[PDB]
Image (tube, rainbow over all chains, first blue to last red; front, side, top):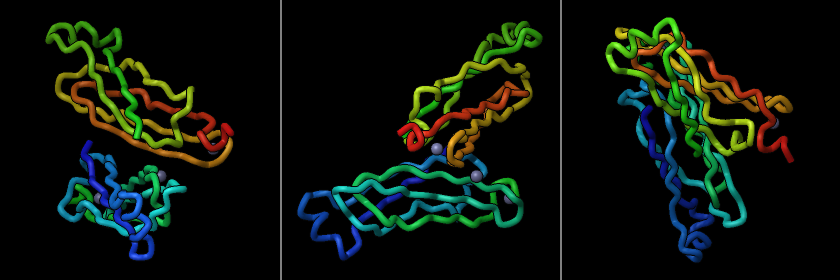
Length: 96
Length: 97
Ligand SMILES: [Zn+2]
Ligand SMILES: [Zn+2]
Ligand SMILES: [Zn+2]
């Protein structure tokens, strides 16, 4: 399977806190299959609220725009919360 | 991010052909989140039909018996086909507690 890299950095609201502890980005790998290797699936760069007391979830959903093929995956991210959800509504590998 | 390894070896009815070409097993893997880091989720070992011209899917499903947490992944495996579906019907990490 293929990996997608997700970059998460602080919202402006939490940037001072994140810089104070010295923790200014998270990088998360998300795995998916060949179905979803397509040009429209690009590595996301997200903004979320840094909080050294919390653990948030990054969720990435894939859905084909022609067929009914879909996939959902989610991973924990230490110290970031209110991570926006990622959606790839694309033409799948096969449908292309 | 936890790797789950899946070992696939030939059924009795296909093992001779697999030995003939010297391809005795496939080791594949999928990934799952912290939700499914529980004792009853363990690397499976499966028997499937060796076939020299096919590519099969192995599917791995997770579902909690207490809440409705669930997860489905799959991976392609060269030369093995009719791979048994793997099902982890378990108590998830949130429901353990
Ligand atoms: Zn499609
Ligand atoms: Zn689903
Ligand atoms: Zn549960």
